[PDB]
Length: 125
Ligand SMILES: CNC(=O)c1cnn(C)c1Cl
Image (cartoon, rainbow, N blue to C red; front, side, top):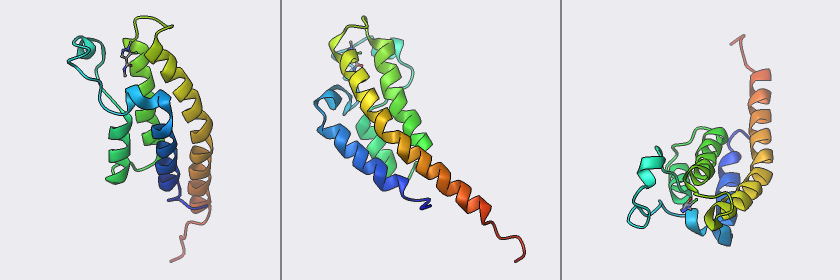
């Protein structure tokens, strides 16, 4: 029932993602000189260095907010790919399955800790 435990769990999961070869295209913002039509397709860029910096700054309030920004990395790759058989999109699907497998217990534990805190609210003092 530790309400704060999610933060270190997300730092460790981000460490595993940065060691995965499949994350290399997603570690830093897309290079607009290499992909000049990227911002004609994609409204909101996102990358794993931005996610880690936001976490380490203390600018996520919950693991649900981190999970929304990681899912945006994957939805941007699906929107920019010219083919569902492309190299970089194929890497995004494998990394998305690994992330979803690991984030599910982080989210469940956080939500369980908040419910336990609300069961024990103090009203008489
Ligand atoms: C992070 N880069 C991308 O998602 C990207 C670049 N090129 N293609 C085909 C994709 Cl998909």
